[PDB]
Image (cartoon, helix red, strand yellow):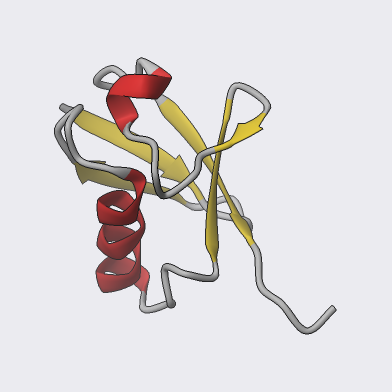
Length: 76
């Protein structure tokens, strides 16, 4: 199922992943797309940060779901 991840800048990145594809898979897809580390990316959905342990299915993310991507890293 295709989806749409909104970048912190506002650009909508179109991708395709299965409900079984864990967040870690989605993140990796984003990196290969724009060119940024996934571990730093943050998938926000339903006002809840998607944990790498979870998966699209858990977030009932259907084809066309709008995922809010945000930056997240240590140091501060």
